[PDB]
Picture 1: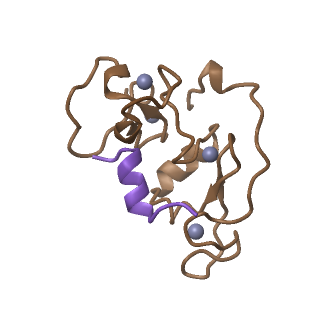
Picture 2: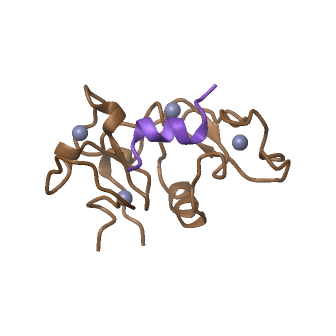
Length: 15
Length: 123
Ligand SMILES: [Zn+2]
Ligand SMILES: [Zn+2]
Ligand SMILES: [Zn+2]
Ligand SMILES: [Zn+2]
């Protein structure tokens, strides 16, 4: 897929 | 020969934050405690190691040449908004720009399954 939601999940959240 | 958008030009660039939002370390230490230069959002200054961002080396190179938006700042390269479906905003695997499915040319209604590259990057 790769969306903004998946990008969050894939990288572990921002700080 | 990478294409830049008119609205991505002559715009203010935020002061880069010298720490990764994901691993909380500098350009001198990634998750492997190895050197890796950061990629920084031109809107808010947020930075991340390409490794922490899960960028391929190819995507890393192209993104560094562009006005990049962090995951939170990313707006649709077509309509310039985040909108109601911002979570579903597609990210280009070639340039990491954002596109709503309905803002793509031609429009999409369902999520592409594998790698996806935008209308700008498509040959
Ligand atoms: Zn990092
Ligand atoms: Zn940002
Ligand atoms: Zn849009
Ligand atoms: Zn693209």
